[PDB]
Length: 50
Length: 50
Length: 49
Length: 148
View 1 (tube, each protein chain N blue to C red):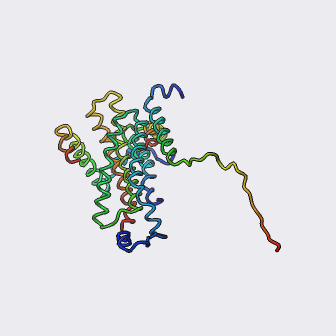
View 2 (view 1 turned 30 degrees about the vertical axis):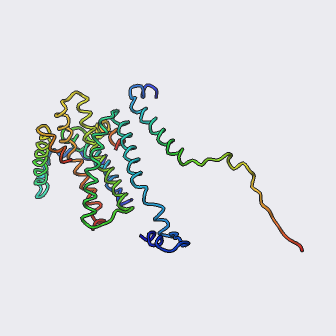
View 3 (view 1 turned 180 degrees about the vertical axis):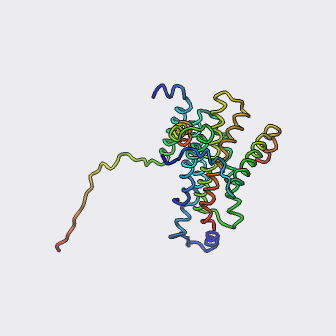
């Protein structure tokens, strides 16, 4: 009920702070996804770290 | 509920293990006696008239 | 315990609201349909947590 | 040490701790038991939830990841392991368990549908990153005034 329909017209916030925050979060999420993929390379390293 | 646990043996095993653990913990803390408080309480009123 | 449990209790609400938001932002569903879909998705996860 | 001292005394004199010392002597040794029983209960609940004896081991391995941080924060500020600390540790264990639960349950469902293991876990992490960071930051700033 409270949630309005998606602000498709607004789309990206394009605020002084929010657009930059979204871009930062997206690129950091890509970096995180790459970092998780490194478990395929050598899981022994992080086992020893654990 | 029978058909539910037929496909989920792990759930039933967890429930059984939990019951066993609770019972085992209870046994080591349960008081032991011949009878419960079966004896009716007695109250004695004593007065002396020399 | 009240203060310490503030984050714990907002966890479930955040999960549900964020799931609805991402569902409607990606699938483009109506808010009611999006809420229904999100509840179907994460009904058991909240119970487990 | 005081018991050693009173032992050094001549015979016939003994000590009996009273009030706060008496109660402190009574308690304080129930911690490790609590932790062990709580961890066992959590493992059993996870086994019930995921219908496996393996997935809980995946979840239960993140308890140390929160315990180490809580211990490091406590020691760094020079605090002490006390009742408040213990309850904190239990809260940290619970939150770490929840954070693990989100990812592992989503990945388990994804691979159950038929997806590749790496693909399933990567997709689950990508989706659940925002809820995890959001909830965790909300909690951290929630207890931030307490720490300061």
